[PDB]
Image 1 (cartoon, rainbow over the protein chains, first blue to last red):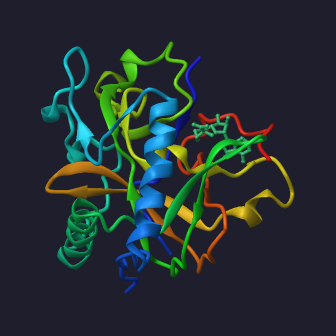
Image 2 (cartoon, rainbow over the protein chains, first blue to last red; image 1 turned 30 degrees about the vertical axis):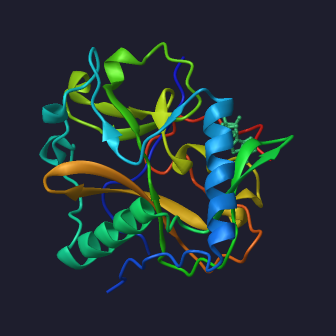
Length: 14
Length: 217
Ligand SMILES: Nc1ncnc2c1ncn2[C@@H]1O[C@H](CSCC[C@H](N)C(=O)O)[C@@H](O)[C@H]1O
């Protein structure tokens, strides 16, 4: 079924 | 202007060797080869598919100042100056990563490495450690990092339970995607000061909600 971790491409770190 | 900080490696060479040994032990357990870079293998995505301009809504660009820090950390890892991290087996989480020395807020931890493949090629994949690389308007162009055969410490870092009232409190680092020389890159950065012995946790569902976390500790 595929589990995928994801992270934003905008907004920086803090 | 929040600047990325280089990590401070453990001063004792024996502590660095021990740290590197726990990572090699975990890689061997998963029958994996160490890889500190994104790899482009046959029957998967070519390096040409990895272009940050394909990211729907664009991607933030890594500054020259932060690229320098990233290059410093990469060069440090090459000579044996790894970040102060320990891969530790936990009965409720499996392999986990803990700080084996202080890690200040805004400190670069690691790049998420492994084989880059098209999301279309991994719809049926059972790998528990897939990480989005590129989310394109055309889904057949979207890429995922697959650390099943090749990878580094990043694949062992735990996630928070996104369903509990207090689970967000465990987050002490963040995963971000930046454009570096026009390509997508995935990095882990500390979001607060982390003490020695403290387990690392970031939000696995930092953009999409494709990771089931209800049962997480
Ligand atoms: N907070 C948490 N509680 C329980 N299990 C967790 C967790 N965070 C991560 N995991 C586990 O780690 C997997 C993601 S990959 C992280 C490395 C893994 N624990 C390993 O032994 O190789 C998840 O599917 C889950 O099994």
